[PDB]
Length: 330
Image (cartoon, rainbow, N blue to C red; front, side, top):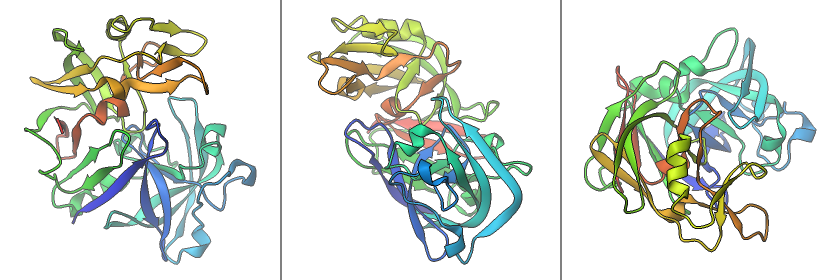
């Protein structure tokens, strides 16, 4: 089997991407944030505290003839941005782009933190990291990909995120029309539960490539590119007037600037992030100070190849017995 679904930016900055997901019988379609940095499929629901729901579409398990309470199971998750959610668990039928899993754990939120409430466009998350990170207790649950894997034509999924435009998540096949050149595969460590790999270096603009190992995670659920402070300083030093602002929380730059590109290495191959992809717009409405899309990972404890990086590539998440990542230009 295979599946193919379009993923759409939630706003004009590509702050996140939403993908429609069918849950239950008859189907209830929710727009979920596919997150290769976590491993829980959780949704706003009829159980979510009413004051914490503000425009989201909810899953109502009592209206699904295939929903079953997973007795005694609870979940609770906290994300790197300080947000969180928790609740109980059902199993139900879940379909993505024509690919169906029966008995998928659907984690129903009883509580969500303010940032989730405040984002009316995201109805929940669909985790695509390794199932060892799943938070369900006392019986850990499998991700949608893990449940589907054995049925797929090939044990893979791909992320093809757009810049200011829709893109695609495919399951079970590699669309050879969706990228240019060849796909370069690179080793993955699953020891922390992430799609963790080592970039071979970077360049800023037309500058020379610096060969240096950068361990980090491929994370579709993180907006920006978080790299070591040395690398990030070298990038922003090429932008007149750019500075790190403690009050804003990162590097800012004059909105009048034209940003240089940023290249990262995948083995001997190179992925080029155009400068425009690094502009996240005014820090507050009407400001002429703009927020940078490349930020320091110091204090986060891990480097994160988030959407800013991934959207410049066609990315293969290869879930073979020894997982690997593939990157192609597009």
